[PDB]
Image (cartoon, rainbow, N blue to C red; front, side, top):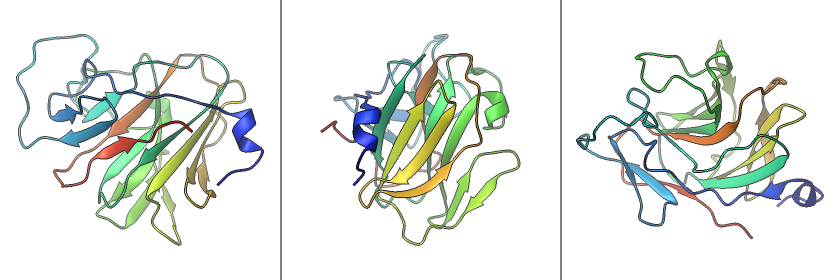
Length: 187
């Protein structure tokens, strides 16, 4: 676990907002888990919804302060998570997931390639695959960090960002597989 960190970072109750979710995503009834469907649902235009990225956001954003949440990634072979700005482009095709486009994310491809989605990408070497990922956000200092949340081991912290928009938790899954992404409860 972590020591002085909790105290400094307020644990956030993150629930997924199905109005943002791409039509290919399946948000659970309790709004804690997201899975990918075999085929898109048929959903009318909604400014909130991601039409290109296979993305869903948390319901609430952050404009100030320090916050922590944990995401259970389990054995899923592909996922990316972090935060993004309120004002990202939700409609346009082929927008790269990068800080410059409003995303601060990391995760896994093909079960074994961990990356921080900087531009260019930063390749990460994990001594053990994490199953739960702790995300620490400090809005004012412009820091977002990722940890293995079960042993508390630091993985990666982005270069400083000066955030000038509200930030959402963001979750991306590209592939169809058995294990969902799940937001862990608070205490």
